[PDB]
Image 1 (cartoon, rainbow, N blue to C red):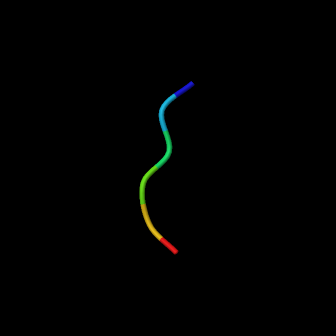
Image 2: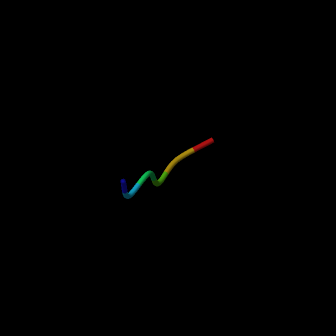
Length: 6
C-alpha cells in the first residue's frame, strides 16, 4: 500500500 496526496 502506497498512497500519496492530501
